[PDB]
RNA sequence: AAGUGUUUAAGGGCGCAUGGUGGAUGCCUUGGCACUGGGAGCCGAUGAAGGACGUAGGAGGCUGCGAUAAGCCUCGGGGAGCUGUCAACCGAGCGUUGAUCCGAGGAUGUCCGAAUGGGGAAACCCGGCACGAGUGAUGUCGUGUCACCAGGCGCUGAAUAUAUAGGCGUCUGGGGGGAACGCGGGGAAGUGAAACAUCUCAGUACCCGUAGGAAGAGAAAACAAAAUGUGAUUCCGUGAGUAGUGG
RNA sequence: UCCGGCUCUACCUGGCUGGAGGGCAGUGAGAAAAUGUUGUGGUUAGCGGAAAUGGCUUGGGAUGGCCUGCCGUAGACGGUGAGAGCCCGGUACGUGAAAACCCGACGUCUGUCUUGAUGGUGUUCCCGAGUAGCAGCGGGCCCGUGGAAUCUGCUGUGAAUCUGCCGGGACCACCCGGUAAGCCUGAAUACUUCCCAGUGACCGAUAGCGGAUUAGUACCGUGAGGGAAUGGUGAAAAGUACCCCGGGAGGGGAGUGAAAGAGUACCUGAAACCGUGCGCUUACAAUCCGUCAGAGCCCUCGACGUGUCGUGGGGUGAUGGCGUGCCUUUUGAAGAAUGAGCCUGCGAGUCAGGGACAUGUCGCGAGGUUAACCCGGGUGGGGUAGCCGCAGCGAAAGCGAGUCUGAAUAGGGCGUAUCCACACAAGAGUGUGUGGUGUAGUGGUGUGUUCUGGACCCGAAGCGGAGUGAUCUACCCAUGGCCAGGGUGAAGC
RNA sequence: CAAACUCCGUGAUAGCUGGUUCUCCCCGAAAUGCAUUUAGGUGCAGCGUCGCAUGUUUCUUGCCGGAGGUAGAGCUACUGGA
RNA sequence: GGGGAUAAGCUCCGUGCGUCGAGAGGGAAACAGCCCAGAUCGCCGGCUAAGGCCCCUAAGCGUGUGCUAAGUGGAAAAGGAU
RNA sequence: UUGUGCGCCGAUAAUGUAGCGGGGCUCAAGCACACCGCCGAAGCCGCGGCAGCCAACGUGUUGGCUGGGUAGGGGAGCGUCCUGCAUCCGGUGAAGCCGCCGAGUGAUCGAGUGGUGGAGGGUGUGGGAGUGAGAAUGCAGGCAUGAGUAGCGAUUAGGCAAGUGAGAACCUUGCCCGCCGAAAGACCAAGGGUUCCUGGGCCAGGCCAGUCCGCCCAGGGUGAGUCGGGACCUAAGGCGAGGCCG
RNA sequence: UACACGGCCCGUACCCCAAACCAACACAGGUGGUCAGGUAGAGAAUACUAAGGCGUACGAGUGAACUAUGGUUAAGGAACUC
RNA sequence: UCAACCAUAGACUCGGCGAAAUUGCACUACGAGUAAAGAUGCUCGUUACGCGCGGCAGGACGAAAAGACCCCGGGACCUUCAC
RNA sequence: GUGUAAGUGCACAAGGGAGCUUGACUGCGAGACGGACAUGUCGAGCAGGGACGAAAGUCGGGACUAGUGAUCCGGCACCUCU
């Protein structure tokens, strides 16, 4: 029973086109070559869906370093003192505070410095 | 490709043309060509063991009986008078089901030739009772002659 | 097209009772002088085919 | 004085609403495909199959028809509607007595076409013979008949003596076309064999001559195997991919 | 039964032909030609053939939705303004042919023969000749010379006629079985250019026949031959009176119509493609053109006033992080290796077989199942013809839970389905004897693989058979035509 | 034109080249040997998969029993070589 | 290890070698085969390997002890040099 | 002299530094040695989700693990067409088209809808398939770009007046100019067959416009005893009764 | 010879070195026979002209390259170049 | 040597009609390096306002033809004391 | 030194001589080695007969490892096969 191949093909044509909506030039017009960049753009989606966490943690660390230096301490020392004091706050909250409440950031850095041992070069 | 009529020649030279290499005006990929796999006249009979069919009938009838869709009757319509109105009155009084199946001794012709018109009713002599009809019908009714002959055939 | 058998094989094998195919020992037709009887002694008396080639042959006999 | 700073779009891109071209998609069937049960299995010298030309009140085309040209008679079925279609339209018109429409028999059937009077580039040239007619007669006109082969019959008979060949004239047949099937004469390669000759492909395709609706085959000089067996041909399913055949 | 004439004549016994009467049958394959016609048989065309204006609603239009009632031996089918048995064509059913034609009998008339027929005791030129068979050569039977019968035939040869022949798979004997060289003869079977009636898990316009349409046309080729594309307005033409722009085309009004974003380029109108407009972006920017972030602007929505919040959206996207298309075949490609201009349709593991096997699964079970075929306008019933396993071993004779090997208990090869408990050995691993558990295959249905078929799809150079061409060219054949003008000056005289 | 053209056998045959279309879930190769008119093909065994069966027989280490004849070393030890 | 010249991204073997093939991630700028390490999916969480911590670019312009003057680091020998 | 760690020379290429990736770095951001740190992946851990295998118990939960993957094997599905069905959906709008929303892990789905469309679709469970396209220099159709680019088809060549007409270089008439003139003139044969003339209009055709045309539309037009082909005869050659051979 | 009679059918248009034929086109090609003026010249070459027909269907404007068709060139005269 | 000028038809601008090959993409620079081993597309650094018109051809391994040569599975034709 | 190269072995001889004589037997073969497969190698014991040695025992070819050829078609001999 010969089946005429119209509706099925058009469904997927339109679905791919819609998913490609908003691309450049003919790339949102020609299905034979929208597929190329639907597939690509989604490959990038897959990869950066994790790349984003790395990038954001990088930005947070940079902001924290800036805040620590403005408060006269280096980021690594801030982290070391904070850990040695056994705080459980992470760098996302660190950065958000550092840009929101400099007073609280100052208090936290004092806590870190106080928890910082006397000698930093001790072999023990 | 072998039966499509005409042009059994190479459409054009092999090399130098710059088009695709072709070898028939009727290739399945060309337009107006033949079909890749041409079907042929064909039969769909499947052979089912006699025990297969007998067991299927026994099962179907057992289920129908458990459902209580069988009856008995001495006669259906008065003789020498095929009258669809009489048949319809009889069936309406008897059953409230629109569609039923009836089995009769073959020789009774008035009943069949009279009640044959309706689309919701069917009549079959029990030599030709079959699984598909039994299943399709909501109910079945066995005349005395038909029930007797069919049961004796079963037990013989 | 009832499946052609292979008359070139049936003249060479026989089906055992459990499904294996018995084959006859080769390398005896001629030049038997410097073949010593001891060599031939395990060389007469048919034997079953190896489980390796049986696959092809089974597809051969009944074809 | 300084440094800080939007402010425009010739065009372009992206979306959104509008449209334009191109005609897929969905839906339709007078068309095709494949079958079943029937019918018919031929048509042709009484001129076939298929064509040219013509044929209408209307210019072309298709359908029918054939100088008697969308047709004519006779017999039977129907009727108040008809003068086929493109295509309409008109215009003329036809019917209660029954016109057209459908069926049966009949006549009509130009020309080419086996073409058959001779010839020929198909639808076109050119004649002989018998009977009538018109012209002052001729001119002229119609009608018919006029091939070949086969088989017979009557007449004739060369070399020549008999007789025969040949020669005439007359009856009866055949001549060509058609999808397959059937018979018969002939009859290959690509291919497989992993090459290739034997071999295979296969007595297939194809060519040719026959008839028929079927044909062909058909009444054992067959098998069988001690049974005091089968009993024409043909076609099915087995027996069986078995016995066998084969670089 | 009788009559006559004959076997060169007339008078007993024996062998034939012709005529008066029972046969054999006949349009016949076995005698030939003639003699003529009845079926409500069919065909060619036809007639009747039931039952709602029913009402209301949407509705342009009803067959539609609801309510009643309808008829049906007819609820196949088509059409009519949307789904109709109660509207029409028509359907079951009934009926019918003046004339002609294909299939079935019956009284004129025709032939024959009863000069022929049936049953019973012994001795002495016919029934298929250049045939059977033969030597050589080849052909068809599964049979390719092989040990090769049977058949046919090309060439040479060549038989017997009953105590004859030829076959019985080299070939011979006893016997065993059937008549060659002459002939014909229905039924079963194959096919469908043609016609009718019905049907389809067949297509629905790039499908389906090449061809739903002026199609084997246009067109291509001088030829043989090839060979197209091209359907739909509407229910109905009611196909756009009239007005206006323009020369017209074209267009806008007006009207038709339910719809004119149905107007003849006419249903639906998509995507590539080309525009208008709107919001946003862009003229310091180096690049598979996106993704992750991301301000701004535009618009949108709710709590909250003039814009701020809010588990906010869509469009845009300034800027920055990462970022070398896709398929191929390859060790390996961003690849400067291949293919793709784009879009839309079409395009590729199908199909048959008691084909074979295995796995699922279904029925029965030491049984499983039927083919063809016959009869039910229907898949039923019958049909055990057949095939597989129940036992294998051996090449075979043959043997048989053993068998083969072999001179062999003497173990080995292959099976005894397969195991449990008891005893005997070595503990060369296991073998040898007892009592029980007792053997599982077969036919569907679907699936992978194999099988022969073109066998997943397109593609070649080429070989062969049948035909079409010497209107160009090659050659030649016959008949015509062509070669302005001006020089040189042989022989001969 | 190194065998004209059209039709037909003809779906000639192609170990060669191209292409082979909807989603998900599970396991997961080799480019080896042998043989091959075989080397760019094919078949057998290894390598994967699914099922069934034996259910650890497999794996790692420790210890034990083992034979080597390599690196190295040696040469009035041989064969050579200085 | 053979061949080649201890040359080739060379060829031919062995590796119960590894990886790519048939593997995404990070590092060596870029780079399958080198180093670290096995991507069921999502999370705007944390700890780490290799490699890194002045800026491009996340991390000490860190601690202490020495060397170097050559931009050696950030291409190379025989030999030569208070 | 010796052993040492660093150094220096030894040191020449080709498009542009181009032999730290670059800036830059000795007041090392270099090298060697130790320490503490900190960054650094899809590794591990953290939270939520899905699925496979496995064990226990039950009549599908708990717990242990594994889940990248080409050739390839296995398992389970989505969707299309057409059949069977209880029979329904729909002119109060089916299919189809274009949007929007929500939902499934996927193929998708929605008795889910907005606008066009105005006549058919079909739940469920089976059954059968011409069943799913991006590629094959695929086929047919449509439309792209090079691009408003190249070309507009000779060597003879025009200007102008007036007329028609909406428009006039291109047509009609007139004046001059140029070109062929053994043709670029005039007759025929072969060939083509209405291209001849007249009248009307200019969509399509003419490589532009076009009143013009060899356009289309209608009408008209071809007059033979003496020219030509048959009545005559024949060449080359073809056909061929009988005949010969196959 | 006075005589009045009697002679078919078919072609007859147009083009026919061309926008009408053969070349897919209104194409710088091919196509057979006949007619053959005047002045120069041997003439059927060539140059200009009558008879007669044409300017064969894109135009208008711009001193660029550069290409093609051509003309001229100081001095040298094959030194280029196979 | 050593080209110069000039008259012609194009090339150019304006009006008219209006093509072809090719084409996966396109918001398409440079150099050194890297790499399937000669990069517009990777790294690094340099330079560069967006867009045209006339030209010139070095690259875009530019276009045309599934490479002739070579080799590999096969054809045809031809030669001969190959069968 | 040990029939024919090299390696492996060999004085308990596998090295010579002699005597005798045929086991360079017949049918099987526990189990193994190698083989992708066809094949290829080793082998204690069982039955008849024989050989050497009184006997013990050894004897199924050469000290081993190369000296080889599948299938078809055919030829020849024997048989308690048809
Ligand atoms: Mg965007
Ligand atoms: Mg095709
Ligand atoms: Mg077709
Ligand atoms: Mg056989
Ligand atoms: Mg032998
Ligand atoms: Mg021997
Ligand atoms: Mg195997
Ligand atoms: Mg006609
Ligand atoms: Mg009548
Ligand atoms: Mg009649
Ligand atoms: Mg008649
Ligand atoms: Mg008549
Ligand atoms: Mg004739
Ligand atoms: Mg005739
Ligand atoms: Mg006669
Ligand atoms: Mg005589
Ligand atoms: Mg005949
Ligand atoms: Mg072969
Ligand atoms: Mg082969
Ligand atoms: Mg053959
Ligand atoms: Mg044969
Ligand atoms: Mg007949
Ligand atoms: Mg017969
Ligand atoms: Mg049989
Ligand atoms: Mg009637
Ligand atoms: Mg209503
Ligand atoms: Mg109703
Ligand atoms: Mg209803
Ligand atoms: Mg109906
Ligand atoms: Mg209806
Ligand atoms: Mg009606
Ligand atoms: Mg034979
Ligand atoms: Mg014989
Ligand atoms: Mg006889
Ligand atoms: Mg006979
Ligand atoms: Mg019959
Ligand atoms: Mg359509
Ligand atoms: Mg032609
Ligand atoms: Mg209205
Ligand atoms: Mg249209
Ligand atoms: Mg429409
Ligand atoms: Mg923009
Ligand atoms: Mg800017
Ligand atoms: Mg950059
Ligand atoms: Mg980019
Ligand atoms: Mg990036
Ligand atoms: Mg980048
Ligand atoms: Mg590869
Ligand atoms: Mg790759
Ligand atoms: Mg490129
Ligand atoms: Mg490539
Ligand atoms: Mg390439
Ligand atoms: Mg390649
Ligand atoms: Mg390309
Ligand atoms: Mg193209
Ligand atoms: Mg099968
Ligand atoms: Mg089964
Ligand atoms: Mg069973
Ligand atoms: Mg039955
Ligand atoms: Mg046997
Ligand atoms: Mg034996
Ligand atoms: Mg025994
Ligand atoms: Mg099936
Ligand atoms: Mg041929
Ligand atoms: Mg000829
Ligand atoms: Mg002289
Ligand atoms: Mg030809
Ligand atoms: Mg054919
Ligand atoms: Mg064939
Ligand atoms: Mg082919
Ligand atoms: Mg093949
Ligand atoms: Mg390829
Ligand atoms: Mg895995
Ligand atoms: Mg264990
Ligand atoms: Mg040791
Ligand atoms: Mg050493
Ligand atoms: Mg030493
Ligand atoms: Mg020594
Ligand atoms: Mg090495
Ligand atoms: Mg290599
Ligand atoms: Mg891996
Ligand atoms: Mg990787
Ligand atoms: Mg990296
Ligand atoms: Mg993982
Ligand atoms: Mg950067
Ligand atoms: Mg930083
Ligand atoms: Mg540090
Ligand atoms: Mg410091
Ligand atoms: Mg120090
Ligand atoms: Mg350096
Ligand atoms: Mg140095
Ligand atoms: Mg020194
Ligand atoms: Mg020192
Ligand atoms: Mg220095
Ligand atoms: Mg650096
Ligand atoms: Mg840390
Ligand atoms: Mg991470
Ligand atoms: Mg993990
Ligand atoms: Mg668990
Ligand atoms: Mg997986
Ligand atoms: Mg691969
Ligand atoms: Mg796979
Ligand atoms: Mg569906
Ligand atoms: Mg509606
Ligand atoms: Mg609507
Ligand atoms: Mg709707
Ligand atoms: Mg509508
Ligand atoms: Mg539907
Ligand atoms: Mg179903
Ligand atoms: Mg289903
Ligand atoms: Mg398909
Ligand atoms: Mg497509
Ligand atoms: Mg693909
Ligand atoms: Mg394509
Ligand atoms: Mg191309
Ligand atoms: Mg273009
Ligand atoms: Mg230009
Ligand atoms: Mg130009
Ligand atoms: Mg021109
Ligand atoms: Mg004018
Ligand atoms: Mg001139
Ligand atoms: Mg001249
Ligand atoms: Mg002249
Ligand atoms: Mg002519
Ligand atoms: Mg003519
Ligand atoms: Mg004219
Ligand atoms: Mg006019
Ligand atoms: Mg006009
Ligand atoms: Mg035109
Ligand atoms: Mg006209
Ligand atoms: Mg004749
Ligand atoms: Mg006269
Ligand atoms: Mg005439
Ligand atoms: Mg004339
Ligand atoms: Mg004329
Ligand atoms: Mg002329
Ligand atoms: Mg033409
Ligand atoms: Mg022209
Ligand atoms: Mg021309
Ligand atoms: Mg000429
Ligand atoms: Mg002249
Ligand atoms: Mg002149
Ligand atoms: Mg003139
Ligand atoms: Mg130029
Ligand atoms: Mg020049
Ligand atoms: Mg001069
Ligand atoms: Mg000079
Ligand atoms: Mg110069
Ligand atoms: Mg010009
Ligand atoms: Mg120019
Ligand atoms: Mg120019
Ligand atoms: Mg143009
Ligand atoms: Mg490099
Ligand atoms: Mg590059
Ligand atoms: Mg480079
Ligand atoms: Mg430019
Ligand atoms: Mg480049
Ligand atoms: Mg180049
Ligand atoms: Mg190229
Ligand atoms: Mg080639
Ligand atoms: Mg080759
Ligand atoms: Mg040839
Ligand atoms: Mg010895
Ligand atoms: Mg010795
Ligand atoms: Mg054994
Ligand atoms: Mg003994
Ligand atoms: Mg022994
Ligand atoms: Mg030995
Ligand atoms: Mg020995
Ligand atoms: Mg052989």
Image (cartoon, coloured by chain):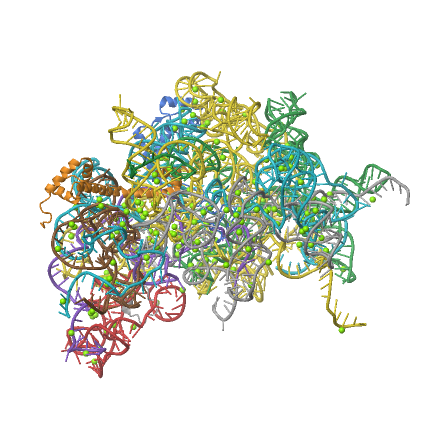
Chain colours: A orange, B blue, D green, E yellow, F purple, G brown, H cyan, K red
Q: Residue at left 36%, top 58%?
A: C9
Q: Nearer the viewer, residue E354 or E99?
A: E354
* Position of residue D189 measured from the top left corner of the image (x, y, whole percent): 49, 58
Visible in this render: residue B126?
Answer: no
State which quarter of the image contains the N terminus of chain A: top left
Compared across the picture, whether H206 is left or right of H22 comes to right
**Picture quadrant of residue D243:** bottom left
Compared across the picture, whether H21 is left or right of H35 comes to right
Seen in the picture, residue E207 relative to B134 is either above or below; the reply is below
**Picture quadrant of residue H60:** top left
Visible in this render: residue B150?
Answer: yes
* Position of residue E260 measured from the top left corner of the image (x, y, whole percent): 49, 27
Q: Nearer the viewer, residue B27 or A12?
A: A12
Compared across the picture, whether H197 is left or right of F17 comes to right
**Picture quadrant of residue C61:** bottom left
Q: Residue at left 45%, top 42%?
A: B41
Ligand 147 falls in quadrant: bottom right
Q: Nearer the viewer, residue C5 or B37?
A: B37
* Position of residue B31 measured from the top left corner of the image (x, y, whole percent): 47, 44
* Position of residue B122 measured from the top left corner of the image (x, y, whole percent): 40, 29
């Amino acid at each position: 029973a010969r089946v005429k191949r119209a509706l099925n093909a058009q469904k997927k044509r339109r679905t791919v086109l819609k998913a490609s909506k908003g691309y450049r030039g003919q790339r949102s017009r020609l299905y034979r070559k929208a597929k190329e960049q639907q597939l690509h753009s989604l490959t990038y989606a897959y990869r950066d869906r994790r790349a984003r966490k790395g990038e954001f943690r990088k930005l947070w660390i940079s902001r924290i370093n800036a805040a620590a230096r403005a408060n006269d301490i280096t980021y690594n020392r801030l982290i070391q003192g904070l850990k040695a004091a056994g705080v459980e706050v992470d760098r996302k909250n660190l950065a958000e505070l550092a840009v929101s409440d400099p007073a609280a950031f100052t208090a936290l850095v004092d806590v870190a410095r106080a928890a910082l041992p006397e000698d930093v070069n001790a072999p023990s | 490709r072998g039966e499509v009529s005409g042009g059994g020649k190479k459409p054009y030279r092999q090399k130098g043309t710059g088009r695709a290499r072709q070898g028939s005006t009727r290739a399945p990929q060309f337009t107006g060509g033949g079909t890749v796999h041409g079907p042929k006249p064909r039969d769909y009979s499947q052979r089912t063991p006699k025990k297969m069919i007998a067991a299927a009938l026994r099962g179907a009838l057992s289920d129908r009986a458990r459902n209580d869709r069988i009856h008995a009757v001495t006669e259906l319509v008065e003789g020498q008078t095929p009258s669809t109105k009489s048949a319809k009155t009889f069936l309406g009084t008897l059953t409230e089901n629109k569609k039923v199946l009836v089995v009769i001794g073959r020789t009774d012709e008035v009943g069949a030739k009279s009640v044959r018109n309706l689309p919701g009713v069917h009549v079959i002599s029990p030599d030709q009772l079959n699984t598909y009809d039994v299943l399709n019908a909501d109910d079945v009714v066995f005349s005395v002659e038909a029930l007797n002959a069919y049961i004796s055939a079963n037990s013989k | 097209p009832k499946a052609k058998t292979h008359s070139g094989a049936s003249k060479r094998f026989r089906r055992t009772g459990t499904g294996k195919i018995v084959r006859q020992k080769a390398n005896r037709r001629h030049l038997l002088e410097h073949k010593p009887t001891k060599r031939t002694r395990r060389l007469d008396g048919r034997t079953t085919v190896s489980a390796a080639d049986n696959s092809r042959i089974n597809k051969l006999l009944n074809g």
